[PDB]
Amino acid sequence: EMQSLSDVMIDFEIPLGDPRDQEQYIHRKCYQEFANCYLVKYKEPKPWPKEGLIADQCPLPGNRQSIWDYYIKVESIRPANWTTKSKYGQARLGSFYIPSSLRQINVSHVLFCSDQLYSKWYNIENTIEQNERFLLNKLNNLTSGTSVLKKRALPKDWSSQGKNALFREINVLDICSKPESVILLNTSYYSFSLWEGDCNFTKDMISPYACRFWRSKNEKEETKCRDGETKRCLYYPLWDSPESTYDFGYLAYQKNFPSPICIEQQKIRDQDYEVYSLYQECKIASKAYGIDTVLFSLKNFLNYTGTPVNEMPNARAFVG
Amino acid sequence: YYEPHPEPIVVKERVLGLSQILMINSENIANNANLTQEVKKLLTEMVNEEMQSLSDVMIDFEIPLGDPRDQEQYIHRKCYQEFANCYLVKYKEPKPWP
Amino acid sequence: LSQISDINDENLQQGIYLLRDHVITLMEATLHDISVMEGMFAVQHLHTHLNHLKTMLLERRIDWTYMSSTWLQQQLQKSDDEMKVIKRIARSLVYYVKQTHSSPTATAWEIGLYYELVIPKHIYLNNWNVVNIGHLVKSAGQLTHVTIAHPYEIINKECVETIYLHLEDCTRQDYVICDVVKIVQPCGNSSDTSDCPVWAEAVKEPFVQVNPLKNGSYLVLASSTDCQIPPYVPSIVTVNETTSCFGLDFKRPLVAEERLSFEPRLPNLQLRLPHLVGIIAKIKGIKIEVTSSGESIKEQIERAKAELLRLDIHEGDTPAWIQQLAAATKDVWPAAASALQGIGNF
Amino acid sequence: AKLRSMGYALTGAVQTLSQISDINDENLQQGIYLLRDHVITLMEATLHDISVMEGMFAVQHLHTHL
Ligand SMILES: *[C@@H]1O[C@H](CO)[C@@H](O[C@@H]2O[C@H](CO)[C@@H](O[C@@H]3O[C@H](CO[C@H]4O[C@H](CO[C@H]5O[C@H](CO)[C@@H](O)[C@H](O)[C@@H]5O)[C@@H](O)[C@H](O[C@H]5O[C@H](CO)[C@@H](O)[C@H](O)[C@@H]5O[C@H]5O[C@H](CO)[C@@H](O)[C@H](O)[C@@H]5O)[C@@H]4O)[C@@H](O)[C@H](O[C@H]4O[C@H](CO)[C@@H](O)[C@H](O)[C@@H]4O)[C@@H]3O)[C@H](O)[C@H]2NC(C)=O)[C@H](O)[C@H]1NC(C)=O
Ligand SMILES: *[C@@H]1O[C@H](CO)[C@@H](O[C@@H]2O[C@H](CO)[C@@H](O[C@@H]3O[C@H](CO[C@H]4O[C@H](CO)[C@@H](O)[C@H](O)[C@@H]4O)[C@@H](O)[C@H](O[C@H]4O[C@H](CO)[C@@H](O)[C@H](O)[C@@H]4O[C@@H]4O[C@H](CO)[C@@H](O)[C@H](O)[C@H]4NC(C)=O)[C@@H]3O)[C@H](O)[C@H]2NC(C)=O)[C@H](O)[C@H]1NC(C)=O
Ligand SMILES: *[C@@H]1O[C@H](CO)[C@@H](O[C@@H]2O[C@H](CO)[C@@H](O[C@@H]3O[C@H](CO[C@H]4O[C@H](CO)[C@@H](O)[C@H](O[C@H]5O[C@H](CO)[C@@H](O)[C@H](O)[C@@H]5O)[C@@H]4O)[C@@H](O)[C@H](O[C@H]4O[C@H](CO)[C@@H](O)[C@H](O)[C@@H]4O)[C@@H]3O)[C@H](O)[C@H]2NC(C)=O)[C@H](O)[C@H]1NC(C)=O
Ligand SMILES: *[C@@H]1O[C@H](CO)[C@@H](O[C@@H]2O[C@H](CO)[C@@H](O[C@@H]3O[C@H](CO[C@H]4O[C@H](CO)[C@@H](O)[C@H](O)[C@@H]4O)[C@@H](O)[C@H](O)[C@@H]3O)[C@H](O)[C@H]2NC(C)=O)[C@H](O)[C@H]1NC(C)=O
Ligand SMILES: *[C@@H]1O[C@H](CO)[C@@H](O[C@@H]2O[C@H](CO)[C@@H](O[C@@H]3O[C@H](CO)[C@@H](O)[C@H](O)[C@@H]3O)[C@H](O)[C@H]2NC(C)=O)[C@H](O)[C@H]1NC(C)=O
Ligand SMILES: *[C@@H]1O[C@H](CO)[C@@H](O[C@@H]2O[C@H](CO)[C@@H](O[C@@H]3O[C@H](CO)[C@@H](O)[C@H](O)[C@@H]3O)[C@H](O)[C@H]2NC(C)=O)[C@H](O)[C@H]1NC(C)=O
Ligand SMILES: *[C@@H]1O[C@H](CO)[C@@H](O[C@@H]2O[C@H](CO)[C@@H](O)[C@H](O)[C@H]2NC(C)=O)[C@H](O)[C@H]1NC(C)=O
Ligand SMILES: *[C@@H]1O[C@H](CO)[C@@H](O)[C@H](O)[C@H]1NC(C)=O
Ligand SMILES: *[C@@H]1O[C@H](CO)[C@@H](O)[C@H](O)[C@H]1NC(C)=O
């Protein structure tokens, strides 16, 4: 539609000043490009510690969930002398494997561009032109001449002085919808287990589903073939398969029935984060160097990894 | 004295004259879009509506070129649009599924 | 022609040349977008396209969806900005619409479209319209309006050089289109300028003409003085404070910001008229040609001399005649005029 | 070749206003007065209807508008 219009209209000089010099042009261009884009800096670099993730709150496949991208499936047919330890390290087959790309040792900052961590001030029920003004005020109120947010803005998890002025707090079900967010930003790993063995919880020690563990431990891991130790051989798993049930932990979490839930905390990162605003840096830098330069400069910073963060899907746009 | 004339002024060298023939066929469109026999009826109603309205305000005009029916590109693109993927298979002798 | 490319041949003339073979196009092939859509989403996208084609053809425009831009530009061998002008001024004709098949689940149609593309020779962007104002002359008692007949209608100025254009056989397809545009020289009394005819016409006294200009000045031509403005010669007038002149209000204009100008500056020109121009314009009772820009004293005089000599004395209006002779003689010999005027009133 | 017309910028002066309201001033004349500052508009903000629509239904509504 745009090209067709472009193809029949020559240019005309109009005797007013250059839009590039007008505030309303600078403010609405920085907004349309960088409104919800932020940069977070760890106190020092520390990655997510394990390659396996126990997270029973998420319903398994049997709506589509984002975490299913990291879900190890239990297969009945395997090759001869096949073991999890060969492929997925110390992960429990039928749970979730975290790749080494999301666990880099040298990553110091996290860059994200989404409107899905804002506290209650933000509502999609309200009007775009309101939700603009609301943000534009808050960012002016929470800043002072630089692009660094005031500690008040952060949630209580990321800072001692945080009061959720801008951002909400990450909850237990957020891992299912927004995996990378949690793995890159959470200060501590909390587990959620209905697996028989964890926290030394024995089947006797309990003082349709009712009081029962989801996955019970079998004798050992083994395969067997019939003169064809290559392609197709039966596999006997070290735990059970949740294909039949697939709602157990999700229904348990919401408390429809009582069950022996296990939860253990493990500290990853210090609660002393620092957060910059790319919308406020665009406004401030454009007053000195002019928007044409600043726009081009900050658009490259969004492509620091090789994939531009602003063109990723809204829930999955988190990069280290 | 003078006043501005904001519209451009074009000096004519020559005129080029062209004839384009546009061919529409619903069945070709229904095959690619995986349509059902109910929606095929909508496609057909919709296309007739628009084409008929245009037909109803335009008289005919003679254009002094040769008949399209004599031109290769007209013969090749008409046979294609009708019979591209149509085939006939002949058994060695008649024998049905047993 | 056997190819579109042949239109640029240098030894062709200004006429209509038809491409010899029809262009055959299937819509299915043209509209890619629909191919990958499914169900009613596909159906509604086609509806939007067919309704837009119909809207263009009613206005006699071309829908460039069904013809490749790269192809047409490659063949025509034109610049990006020439193509924009070519595609804006082209016009369409629907010469047949035929339904070729009609089932309850299936249809097929054919449309014959005929296009006429104007190929430009030159494009002119920075243009002015001429407005002739003229000059008043008071001659042997009669007030007369005098005008030059300029051989151009448009002044053009792209950068620094000014150009005077004479247009012929023009129409409007968004822009003005002309078959003939001749470049001319402005009027003068020299070998390197135009020798233009000069028209005179009798007018009623008192004469007043005031045109408000858009920039906030006023154009004045008047047979009598007011607010210090000289009579008979026209002028562009501006005031620093609102005042009433020629029975209407001349307001102070709003301060403006200065930009780069493209205003033309015509050459100046002295013009000698016949002594009795007022009597010549009066006895015709229509607007009449009295000289050329570059005419000799001898030719100019031998032009209304026989006509003027044969306005002789008569038995039936001697007093009315004698009063004309005085008005004619006043500037030449004031002593004789006063005498003749006396013998008139006696 | 690169065309660009001065058809609306030919005279070498310009009379500008600071507000649309200023056009009704009684001691102005009959001419062209330009508002001094551009009006900046985002379509996303203008078209509310699309905001609440989803999938291809959103896409087809924008197509009709464009
Ligand atoms: C509303 O709109 C109207 C327009 O529609 C406005 O009216 C216009 O307002 C203009 C002001 O912006 C006026 O321009 C000014 O004209 C002055 C007078 O120009 C004439 O005299 C000049 C001097 O002549 C004497 O001195 C020289 C030696 O210096 C002797 O040789 C002479 O014999 C004289 O003694 C003279 O230079 C000019 O000559 C040029 O124009 C005539 C035709 O008019 C030509 O025949 C000439 O060839 C010549 O034109 C050519 O050459 C000159 C350079 O020499 C080029 O500029 C031309 O493009 C062309 O090639 C005139 O005879 C100027 O004095 C005055 O100059 C100012 O600006 C210059 C820079 O441009 C400075 O250097 C000066 O110092 C000075 O500041 C200016 O040009 C318009 O005349 C006027 N138009 C009309 C039709 O009336 C109106 O204001 C608007 N109203 C509102 C409210 O906005
Ligand atoms: C990423 O980071 C976010 C934080 O921003 C994190 O979300 C939090 O997740 C934790 C862990 O699930 C949540 O805390 C738990 O809440 C449970 C429910 O809270 C209600 O009940 C308590 C009283 O019991 C009330 O005070 C409260 O107001 C609520 O009504 C609560 O049951 C949990 O408490 C148990 O677990 C902790 C573990 O440290 C333990 O200290 C407690 O003593 C308590 O007992 C333990 O019970 C478990 C079984 O339930 C048992 O295994 C264990 O042996 C017991 N331990 C002892 C010593 O007896 C706990 O407080 C928190 O609410 C979430 N925050 C928010 C804001 O939603 C994500 O989980 C992180 N995601 C990932 C993937 O890392
Ligand atoms: C266009 O431009 C032309 C050229 O300027 C204008 O015509 C001339 O007008 C002027 C001013 O009115 C005339 O000036 C006078 O010249 C005579 C002498 O003329 C004789 O010598 C000339 C020498 O060059 C010659 O060209 C003349 O030839 C013409 O005339 C003869 C005879 O009729 C004819 O046969 C030819 O074919 C030519 O047409 C001629 O031989 C001179 O005596 C005058 O002197 C008076 O003025 C001066 C200065 O004020 C003063 O000092 C004296 O005391 C005296 O009062 C005067 O200089 C000139 O003759 C005209 N030339 C022509 C060719 O006609 C013309 O008016 C312009 N047209 C328009 C429409 O504006
Ligand atoms: C009629 O013609 C007049 C020319 O004879 C016009 O007068 C000129 O109008 C301009 C308006 O911009 C004045 O410019 C102002 O100048 C003063 C300061 O004066 C000094 O500086 C200027 C150059 O800026 C210089 O030209 C002077 O000689 C002085 O040295 C500033 O305070 C203003 O902001 C503005 O720039 C000209 O000064 C003035 N020129 C003269 C010779 O008077 C008059 O405007 C015309 N009137 C109408 C009714 O149109
Ligand atoms: C109309 O319906 C047909 C029939 O279903 C559609 O064709 C199918 O398109 C899908 C998606 O592109 C194909 O699935 C994919 O195939 C590739 C290649 O084998 C594979 O790598 C993917 O994992 C996936 O299986 C599918 O092959 C193809 N049909 C068949 C029978 O194979 C067509 O897309 C529909 N047209 C539309 C929506 O316009
Ligand atoms: C695009 O997708 C998002 C994500 O699903 C949609 O947002 C969701 O909208 C629904 C319906 O408005 C919300 O559900 C309702 O929430 C209210 C308030 O908590 C509650 O009272 C209702 O019982 C119901 O649960 C939902 O909250 C919201 N998303 C999330 C994650 O909470 C959005 O509507 C979609 N955009 C469209 C269709 O244009
Ligand atoms: C984002 O960064 C990547 C990596 O530098 C860019 O990828 C290059 O793209 C150009 C396109 O002309 C190719 O010629 C290069 O070969 C690409 N390099 C690699 C390693 O893939 C990418 O263009 C950038 N994208 C944007 C939008 O700026
Ligand atoms: C990470 O940083 C360390 C210390 O600077 C360096 O030795 C190492 O090469 C870097 N890269 C990786 C992948 O460890
Ligand atoms: C029991 O739990 C404690 C937790 O500190 C652990 O150290 C110990 O190894 C566990 N013992 C058994 C037998 O599982």
Image (cartoon, rainbow, N blue to C red):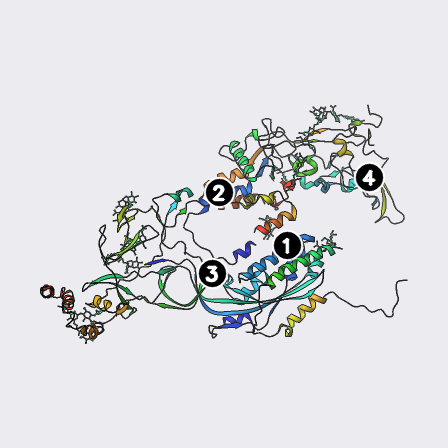
* Residue B36 visible, this angle: no
Tell me, yes or no, whether dots 1 and 2 are on the same chain: no
C52 and C19: which is toward the camera:
C52
Q: Chain of mark 2?
A: A
- Check residue A244 in the rendering and tell me which mark sits there, or answer none: 4
Tell me, yes or no, whether dots 2 and 4 are on the same chain: yes
For label 1, count other residues whose C-alpha is less than 10 Å away and answer few (under 14), some (14-19) or many (20+): some
Q: Chain of mark 1?
A: C
Ligand 5 is in which quadrant of the figure? bottom right
Q: Where is mark 2, residue-wise?
A: A26
**Marks 1 and 4: which is nearer the front?**
1
Horizontal relation, residue A14 to residue A78: left or right:
left
Q: Position of residue C318 (x, y in %)?
A: 14, 69
**Marks 1 and 2: which is nearer the front?**
1
**Marks 4 and 3: which is nearer the front?**
3
How far apart are the alpha carbons under marks 2 and 4? 57 Å
Say which quadrant the C terminus of chain C sits in: bottom left
Q: Residue at x 23, y 65 (%)?
A: C271
How far apart are the alpha carbons under marks 1 and 2? 36 Å
Per the image, label 3 sits on a secondary structure element best described as: loop
C289 and B64: which is toward the camera:
C289
